Amino acid sequence: NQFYSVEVGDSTFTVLKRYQNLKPIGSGGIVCAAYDAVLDRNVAIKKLSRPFQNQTHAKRAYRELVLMKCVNHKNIISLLNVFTPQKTLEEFQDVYLVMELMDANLCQVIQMELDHERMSYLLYQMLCGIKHLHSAGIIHRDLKPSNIVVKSDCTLKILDFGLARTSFMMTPYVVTRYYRAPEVILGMGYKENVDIWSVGCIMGEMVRHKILFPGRDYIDQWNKVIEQLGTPCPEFMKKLQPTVRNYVENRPKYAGLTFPKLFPDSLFPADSEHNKLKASQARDLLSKMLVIDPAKRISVDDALQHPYINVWYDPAEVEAPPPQDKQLDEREHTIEEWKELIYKEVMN
Ligand SMILES: COc1cc2c(cc1Cl)C(c1cccc(Br)c1)=NCC2
């Protein structure tokens, strides 16, 4: 048998014999660190249990399997291996995904104090990933630090591909909503720079070491947004559904704090002239990203050319090739049907 099983937490991991020494690293997909004897290197292994179990699990598992293939960029996840220990479609239960192991998630990194060099390099890489996604026709809409990983050398990868076209799940785990753009919160149409919002949230948490827009749900969250950024102006409301527009115009109204107030000099390295200049530059970029109205929010291409960001700028990394299904995102199936779609993709 080419497989063996081991208990990793209260999960069984049945994996190819090449992967040894499974240490758990993730939960909520369960994720392990292992050593790959064939490649003589460390890897992350993630187990999807019955990913065909419902539409939500299935749409995501399937979509991200196929989207893996038409994407190739150092700032986006790529798989080393995909396998199932089960021998037939009938017996099929689990998919395991393998990638090169990384050192930390972005949550852990946000907790640290970081110089402008590492901070701006992280942000540059997020923009490169997002640009590559956009160039392939993928608007993420759901970036969060928990799905971003870093190596010690500050290299970065995005691990998921966001939302599709919902959506109920009987699990006790919560969806993190804090990085979603106003237009996602308020059910608007969106464009590429929806993902710029998420980046500002992350950048801002890196400075503040505190989630920018928290809340039980979108009600609390929207309050957190207008009380810091202030009520959006008339022409923003005009693009809201008449029902959403009513509720938004009827909330307590705010002037909104300035960006020096939101992010004082005290939060920044500002001990040399270099850092004083970078502080101003960081704040200026934040002020252009954390913009409620997407018509005035900065684009990915403009953010890449921002002074804070452009010191890293590489044509290789920015204007990388956009390769390579179609009706993916809009498809609707049953358990039986998603099981086979998934099995086919795991087996090729
Ligand atoms: C610290 O290293 C990691 C930590 C995690 C993950 C990947 C890596 Cl490389 C994944 C992940 C995500 C997709 C596929 C695979 Br394989 C792994 N999820 C969150 C924890």
Image (tube, grey):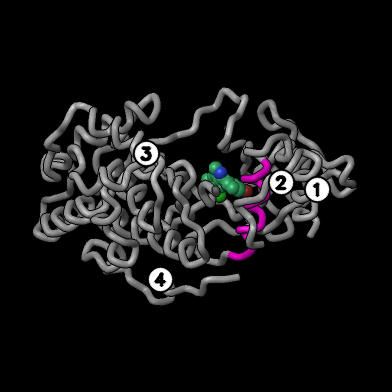
Total labels: the figure holds 4
The alpha-carbon separation of the residues under discs 3 and 1 comes to 36 Å
The alpha-carbon separation of the residues under discs 2 and 1 comes to 16 Å
Identity of the residue drawn at 37% across and 52% down: 194
Choose the circle earlier in sequence order: 2 or 1: 2
Choose the circle earlier in sequence order: 3 or 4: 3
Image vertical order of residue 79 relative to residue 95, above or below: below
Choose the circle earlier in sequence order: 3 or 2: 2
Q: Residues within 10 Å of mark 4 (few under 14, many from 20)?
A: some
Tags 2 and 1 in contact by the CB under 8 Å rule? no
Q: Which residues are magenta?
A: 58-70
Q: Position of residue 258 (x, y in %)?
A: 11, 43
The alpha-carbon separation of the residues under discs 4 and 1 comes to 37 Å
Image vertical order of residue 236 relative to residue 322, above or below: above
Residue 42, can we see it?
no
Disc 2 residue type (three-letter): Tyr
| The one of 165 and 323 positioned closer to us in this rendering | 165
Marker disc for residue 186: 3
Q: Position of residue 227 (x, y in %)?
A: 20, 32
Q: Secondary structure at mark 1?
A: helix
Marker disc for residue 318: 4
Q: Secondary structure at mark 3?
A: loop
Disc 4 residue type (three-letter): Val
Choose the circle earlier in sequence order: 2 or 4: 2
Magenta stretch contains residue 289: no
Identity of the residue drawn at 66% across and 54% down: 65
Residue where numbered disc 1 is placed: 340
